[PDB]
Image 1 (cartoon, rainbow over the protein chains, first blue to last red):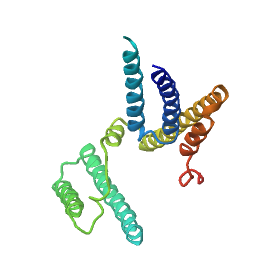
Image 2 (image 1 turned 180 degrees about the vertical axis):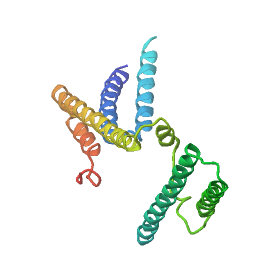
Image 3 (image 1 turned 45 degrees about the horizontal axis):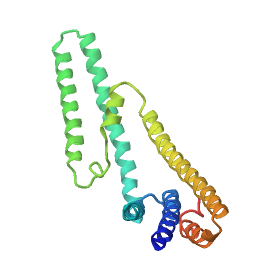
Length: 56
Length: 157
């Protein structure tokens, strides 16, 4: 499961970077926010699904 | 832009001559009002009142058929409901213009405050991300560069 744990770290870092990018997009033009919210949505469900895979 | 300039010139001319026509209508109104208030009952006074109604009807004729005239910006000029009810309330419509353009500047400044607060959040959070995680320096710099692109609609004030 070490691959999943490092993937979880990578997903956390990607979520933080995606939040920072969302703040940048909101700070210059809040009309392409839909794809960034979608990316945060899929990053979060990937994080939660990796936790559910680690649950057994 | 030449067409807009010249048609706004006939806007100004058409509004000025309608000022004249409406003022003439109000002057006809003041004279039949004083006719009612000091009516002597003479047939000459009655015929003068009849001619007053004649001139009122033909002034309304001219301005109504000119409201249906194609050679007119009477239709191209636009009127909303708030200014007409505001004048009906007895209040000065230049205050309506003032409040509306001040609302323009309020929304511009409020959205600009949103943008600058979001920029403060962005660069403070980016600096703290770089300070905490030294391996995120390149992605944060890429994100800041991409979310601060080349300025084409920000260099000008």
